[PDB]
Image 1 (cartoon, rainbow, N blue to C red):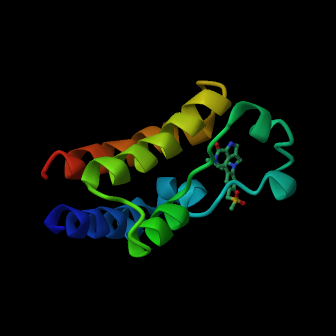
Image 2 (image 1 turned 45 degrees about the vertical axis):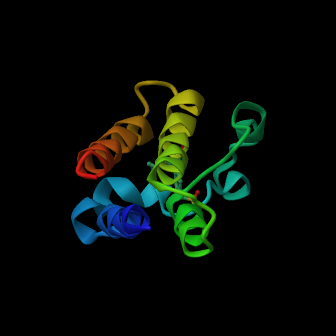
Length: 107
Ligand SMILES: Cn1cc2c3c(c[nH]c3c1=O)CN(CC1CC1)c1ccc(CS(C)(=O)=O)cc1-2
């Protein structure tokens, strides 16, 4: 699909140096053990991160751009659900979501 190729472009933008200052906590799965977030799995039923989405896209796990978009939004929603609203990581998620929503709207 043409729109799935657009999804590869979306990930390249989200992983780019321009956005690294706020995107970096979303690059890989939340490491509950190293971070001491032992209540994370009690709140978050479906963890998601950018590396997992990249692997799913490459393995043809998304039928269309809407399925890809749902996993990106799941990653943001997990952050908004788990953390207090004033947390530094929530502000970072919002800045990354701005990048994603503007690009996703172009297709
Ligand atoms: C998505 N996310 C991510 C983090 C996180 C934290 C609390 N709540 C979340 C959350 O919701 C603690 N901090 C926040 C960070 C300073 C701004 C870190 C630190 C390192 C990593 C990468 S890792 C591979 O070591 O997990 C992730 C996260």
